[PDB]
Image (cartoon, coloured by chain):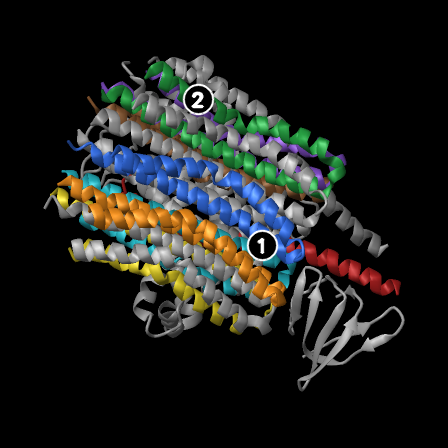
Chain colours: A red, D brown, E purple, F green, H blue, I orange, J cyan, L yellow
Amino acid sequence: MNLNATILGQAIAFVLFVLFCMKYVWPPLMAAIEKRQKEIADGLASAERAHK
Amino acid sequence: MNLNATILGQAIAFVLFVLFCMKYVWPPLMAAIEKRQKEIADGLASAERAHK
Amino acid sequence: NLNMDLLYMAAAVMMGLAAIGAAIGIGILGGKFLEGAARQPDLIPLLRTQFFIVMGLVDAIPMIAVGLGLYVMFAVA
Amino acid sequence: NLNMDLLYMAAAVMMGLAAIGAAIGIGILGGKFLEGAARQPDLIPLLRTQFFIVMGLVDAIPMIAVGLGLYVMFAVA
Amino acid sequence: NLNMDLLYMAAAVMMGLAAIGAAIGIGILGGKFLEGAARQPDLIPLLRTQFFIVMGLVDAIPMIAVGLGLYVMFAVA
Amino acid sequence: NLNMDLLYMAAAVMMGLAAIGAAIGIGILGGKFLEGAARQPDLIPLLRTQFFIVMGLVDAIPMIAVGLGLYVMFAVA
Amino acid sequence: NLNMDLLYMAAAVMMGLAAIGAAIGIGILGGKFLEGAARQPDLIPLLRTQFFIVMGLVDAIPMIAVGLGLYVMFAVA
Amino acid sequence: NLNMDLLYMAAAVMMGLAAIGAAIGIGILGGKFLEGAARQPDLIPLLRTQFFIVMGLVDAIPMIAVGLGLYVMFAVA
Amino acid sequence: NLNMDLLYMAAAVMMGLAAIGAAIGIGILGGKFLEGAARQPDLIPLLRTQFFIVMGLVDAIPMIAVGLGLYVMFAVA
Amino acid sequence: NLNMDLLYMAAAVMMGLAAIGAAIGIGILGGKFLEGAARQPDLIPLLRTQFFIVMGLVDAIPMIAVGLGLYVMFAVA
Amino acid sequence: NLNMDLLYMAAAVMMGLAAIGAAIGIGILGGKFLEGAARQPDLIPLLRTQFFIVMGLVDAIPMIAVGLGLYVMFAVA
Amino acid sequence: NLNMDLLYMAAAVMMGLAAIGAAIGIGILGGKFLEGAARQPDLIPLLRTQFFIVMGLVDAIPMIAVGLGLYVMFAV
Amino acid sequence: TYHLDVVSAEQQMFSGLVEKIQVTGSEGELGIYPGHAPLLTAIKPGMIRIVKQHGHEEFIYLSGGIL
Amino acid sequence: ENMTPQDYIGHHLNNLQLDLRTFSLVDPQNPPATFWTINIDSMFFSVVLGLLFLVLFRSVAKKATSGVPGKFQTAIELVIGFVNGSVKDMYHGKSKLIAPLALTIFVWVFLMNLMDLLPIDLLPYIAEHVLGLPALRVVPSADVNVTLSMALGVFILILFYSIKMKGIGGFTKELTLQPFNHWAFIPVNLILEGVSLLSKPVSLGLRLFGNMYAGELIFILIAGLLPWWSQWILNVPWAIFHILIITLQAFIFMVLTIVYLSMASE
């Protein structure tokens, strides 16, 4: 259809949602998920070590 | 054309679409979530059994 | 006047040929992807990754064509 | 006003080429799906999933073509 | 004179391309079906049930073009 | 006069496309039928049954195109 | 002019597309015939009988266009 | 009068399409003939008979088309 | 004037379609000949003989086309 | 005037053919890529390099067509 | 002026169709040559010689078309 | 006038059909090249040579078609 | 070069490294250079050509088998 | 209300443009000429949906627990691991940007497409009558300007990473020498690889635009042409298919973004 200035206004909205997401959203969620994964992995690892 | 009749037909079609969704699309999502909480509980159960 | 008659036909030719090209390219590629998935299940995710790698390249020119046909239809005519 | 008949032809060509593309792409794809089922008949519900995942792409451009042809044939004409 | 004539030309092109599309697509699909039936005949009642599903999708889009060609010929005259 | 003289050309287009579509579809289908009959010669009467089953679906769209082409030539023009 | 010359063009289209279809479909079908005859050099009569069975159906619908093109040229023009 | 050129155009179309079909169908059939002959190199006197048996059918409609093209060119025009 | 001009196009179509048919048919047949040669290199002098035997049939019609094209371009011009 | 209406049609045909060509060529090339990965997926990093090496040439000309089509549509207009 | 504007289209049809035919025929033949050479690296020169022999047959008619298209475009103008 | 716009239409036909040919034929050839490379991964440098050898004759005609398209387009 | 083994059900018929071989595979003559992709095929009775490292050709007669 | 069906279908394809020369609303009947006329309906629904995404994810990222997660936390972490695996499957560099970029792309485009499902004339009717606005269309992804906006952002990332991770020297070598590998073919090589570089972002944006535009345009047609008592039997079988389309057209955007950014550096 018709190109518009909106292609420029939307580039502001895009970049800003990527920075706030990158900083606040992603790092903590991945931190929590990895914190669960590590605990179960190493707990069972300790379990099989003591068994032997 | 009458515009009210169009708003009637769209409402009918949206009701029908929602009624499809509830009984084919939503149950799978809740099943996935429930099964991932089952998995996570068991995996915490694994660490509890390992301490035992 | 004389404009819209021919401009609609131009957009029509453009998007018809685009539809032929993208449909046939993806049909071949997906047929090979499905034979590969039937050959070796448990690789479905990796083959699907590669399938999208290629499908992204297949549809480029057809999608420029679709975009410019819609441009002609709703911008020029 | 001669305008209308030509618009009907522009819609006819769009929908015809779309029909060819979307028919032959899905034919090639479903042929591979079926030969895959013949080998691993218990996997059918998984290959149906992959087949519907891929078929949504074959019908990307052909269905846009059908939409715009049906538009020109009615909305514009 | 030539207004009503050309509508028939657009219906002709539309239905001709729709016929090629559906014909070639179901030809390929049924060819692969027959091959799977040949390789495992005791499995035919299942491959046929899957063949009809796929065939429904294949011809689906050629058949609205068939409907619109019949519309153009008779209804629009 | 041009009006019906061109209807003759419209039927020509329609049923020539129908002819090639049905011919090639049945050619592919029959080629696969013959390969199946060659792999399991004890099985021919069954595969031929299935072949006739699906060959009715192949030509179904071609056949109405043939009917309408003949109509346009004899009835209309 | 417009009366006689176009009818020859309609016959030309009819009997060119009929030629395309009736040639390529039988080429495809006979390729599998000759492959079967190379796999099972004893079955050749049975497979050629099946080949004619299917080839009648293959060639049938082009021949409608063939007779109709001869009609258009001689009977009409 | 100008009419005479469209007759040459019509014969050009008709004979070109007949040449396309008569070339490609026999190309396929001969490709399979050679593929079968490389396997069983002593069955050439038999496969080469079956080859002509089928090839007689391929070229028929193309031959009708070619003869009618020649008639249109020299006799009518 | 057009009696001069159009004829160059009417031979153009003839010698385009002749070239496509001959190139594609001989490409297929020579490809099969080559794969046969790679597998049975000892049979090369036999498969070459049979290849030349068959090529003269595919080359049959395309040379009618090309000679009539040269004629029309230079003879009637 | 007629210039822009015809120039849009020229660009439309050029980009349409370009899209068909590039899409189907990359579709074949990618189908072969995916089958070669399906047999042994540790050569994915290597076959996926040779794939781009060849796709760069497959899509050489089609972008010459796109490049000039865009020019005609936006520069000659 | 009015005369010359159509001979460039007469050349265009010849050379577009000849480029398609020659390109695709040599593509097939070279693909089979590379397959046979990938089976047997030791026969590569013999297969290369047979390839070049058949390839001369491949592009004869296409090259007649190229010569005549260049003639029309630069000698009849 | 009517003269020039038809020149661009013929140039477009030439340069589109040349694109069809040069894409489809090199796709058909490169597919076989790739599977052969996946088969004899050591002979890749050997097979690529022959691949270019044949690629040249594949491109033979499409390049003439392209040059005449550019001629018709800009040079007349 | 790669390592070739020709073994019967009874005794070993050959071993060592090789540059290449040529076998008459079931679907047609065939040649295995190094790094060849994993392949499995029956082979028809006849001679199998070996060229041992340093180009030393030798022929073994094989009544058939699976490669 | 003299809506002819060809005119009702017309009004629905009208954006609610505001002119930046005078901050005034561009009326549908006459469209002013300028590049300075923001489409307001979409940018709102776009910023609003990105805000809804970010708020939903943040009200959990600030609380997520490593015990048995809640039924809502689980839904978010599911998609987190999904995008994270899609990234790990197609990217091995150390850049922290790629994963959140792909997450935002996937979820935001998915929500924008989701607008397509609602009854076409609900919010437009409320927007005309209740508020008074002249026109409204509520699908952000069915407009050119937003889609190519994201495509150009990802294009600038393509260039940034292509320069950073292999420097101007390797970048200029790749652009010129490939694919024919001889310095004789450099002049042509720049055109092919140059546009082919340009092809990626343009095609990225148009893949989404065309699909969402022409999937909306159907609901406008089915709504306008068919009588109310016949609309459902052609509407619902279309929405059931667009539910697949909206998912695939966001997932493909995410995947191709990841691919272009990872194949640029490595």
Label 1 resides on the chain identified as H
Q: Quadrant of the N terminus of chain N?
A: top left
Can you give x and y, in whole percent of width and height, for residue N85 in the image? 59, 54
Left or right: L51 in relation to F45: left
- The quadrant holding residue I50 is bottom right
Which numbered marker is on residue A47?
A: none
Disc 1 from disc 2: Cα separation: 45 Å
Can you give x and y, in whole percent of width and height, for residue D71 in the image? 35, 27
- The secondary element bearing badge 1 is classed as helix
Identify the amino acid type marked 1. Answer: Leu
Can you give x and y, in whole percent of width and height, for residue I4 in the image? 16, 43
Q: Is residue F21 above or below residue N91?
A: above
Can you give x and y, in whole percent of width and height, for residue D53 in the image? 56, 41
Do residues under tags 1 and 2 come within 8 Å of each other at their CB atoms? Answer: no
Pointer 1 local density, CA inside 10 Å: few below 14, some 14–19, many at least 20:
many
Label 2 resides on the chain identified as E
Identify the amino acid type marked 2. Answer: Gly
Residue A38 visible in the picture: yes
Q: Which residue is mark 1?
A: H34
- The secondary element bearing badge 2 is classed as helix
Pointer 2 local density, CA inside 10 Å: few below 14, some 14–19, many at least 20:
few
Left or right: N137 in relation to N106: left
Q: Nearer the viewer, residue I35 or E75?
A: I35
Which numbered marker is on residue E67?
A: 2
Q: Residue at 57% across / 27% down in the picture?
A: F57
